[PDB]
Length: 88
Image (cartoon, rainbow, N blue to C red; front, side, top):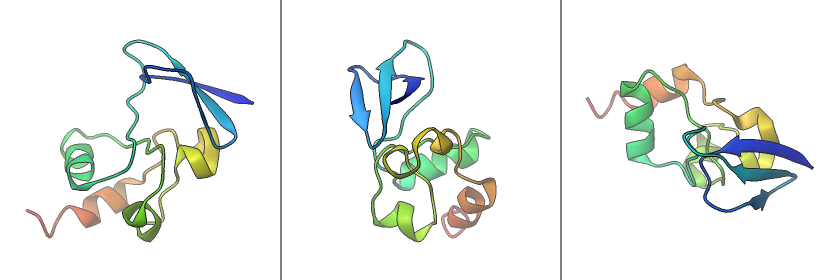
């Protein structure tokens, strides 16, 4: 199984990969929401969503549960920017 060093608190199996606890590592979004997308737009950052919901699917986003290590900071900037502008 593939391994991801991230900010999880317990060792967890998500899909076909494993999240291992590492302090001050990669931030993990459990399920994407409005605040997560608003913060990624402001922080000049991407997102690593761990489990999918309706919003992540309709935005065509990759999650750790469905895409493994490929979801690491995989949320494109055009998606974050286009979602967040009706709210500014």
